[PDB]
Amino acid sequence: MAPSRANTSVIVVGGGGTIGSSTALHLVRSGYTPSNVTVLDAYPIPSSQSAGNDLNKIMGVSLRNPVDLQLALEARQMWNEDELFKKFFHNTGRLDCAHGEKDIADLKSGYQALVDAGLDATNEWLDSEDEILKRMPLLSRDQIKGWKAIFSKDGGWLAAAKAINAVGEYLRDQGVRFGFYGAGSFKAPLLAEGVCIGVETVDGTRYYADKVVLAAGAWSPTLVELHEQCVSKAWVYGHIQLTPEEAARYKNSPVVYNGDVGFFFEPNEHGVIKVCDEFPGFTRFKMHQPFGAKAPKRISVPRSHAKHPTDTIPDASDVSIRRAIATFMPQFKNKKMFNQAMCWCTDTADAALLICEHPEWKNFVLATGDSGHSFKLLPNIGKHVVELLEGTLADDLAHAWRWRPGSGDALKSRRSAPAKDLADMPGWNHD
Ligand SMILES: *Cc1cc2c(cc1C)nc1c(=O)[nH]c(=O)nc-1n2C[C@H](O)[C@H](O)[C@H](O)COP(=O)(O)OP(=O)(O)OC[C@H]1O[C@@H](n2cnc3c(N)ncnc32)[C@H](O)[C@@H]1O
Image (cartoon, rainbow, N blue to C red; front, top):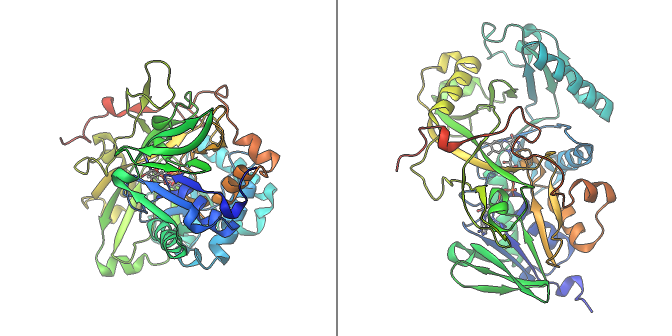
């Protein structure tokens, strides 16, 4: 008979990242014995190459699939109420802006979706630049002519790296096992009679456990064969440095986002503003054999800034981010960004997660397909990964997250175009 929860060992591969750390946290909260939980990652939590290892991420409700509502409301509750997470949510609001006929129309129906989901109380439609300027006076009336926006009072930003670090300190304090670098870089599951019984890492270390969760983010489809269910893509950011006096003016600013321009956050405690552009992401295709492939594979394999710290971003991305600064912060349009880097996610065709047992390898569970929208789910997502492990996952979540090679084209996903490839986007490589 299977061991009880208290005696069930679980390896979380990618446990130094977002979904992995959340899964480990929820194993412990659910009453798995901490010393039976092993967190393996290529890098110490929060992993240097985790998409969650950043200054900030946006918190808000965005409804791309039906399950998104439950998941966002769960996350919102915990960012507000959970003592582990609360201090890292800054509830400054989110300004979701659009300009142009198409983008405005899409935003208007998006607003109605929020209303229809029951969130009328915390979302307001701003129908002119004058209304936007009321919610953030530091935007330039010259740059935002003809813009409209949704203002979400319940949104804001998340101190992402700090939050994962706090989870790591919880796990450490509880007695969770850690393996990093050579001792944490997964290469293969260990299989016996079609059951997964552990993993082996690049340095030959073998870990044995009753269950294994693969929460390896953008690396997931590089590590095991996923039949193009997830296609990994990079997005980009840069940092600019403000004087203390400049930074003080921006204190408690709402997050500002425009799907056609990018987004930016208030300065952190060091006076640094992080800026992203917005675009369909970049692949980096190369020949690579994930465990379980039965033919030659060309797949998008992350070019990791952690492994290649002299990398920056494509020239085109430097241009686009600078255009975002010129639009959002014209007074800063001549600052030189630094710490430019690529940040990796993996898209499913429908932008819902991939959280399911492997169809052949019993007790090996996928927990990936983050689709560029999942940091905000740090507090809660692990709860549902545990439910999946235990066979108690609700039908709607399980269906949305199921193994689905048939589902569609992840290279385009729900985005405006198929991602371009870093091979065709010069300027990031300084080898
Ligand atoms: C890139 C990005 C993403 C992003 C964003 C802006 C950028 C530039 N803005 C967001 C926002 O405003 N709000 C939001 O909610 N999300 C936003 N995103 C997306 C978000 O960052 C991601 O969706 C999410 O963080 C991904 O979580 P996931 O757990 O899937 O991925 P990860 O945190 O990168 O963790 C993966 C871990 O796996 C480890 N790894 C890799 N290979 C191995 C091996 N071989 N063995 C063991 N571990 C491995 C990595 O080290 C990593 O820690």
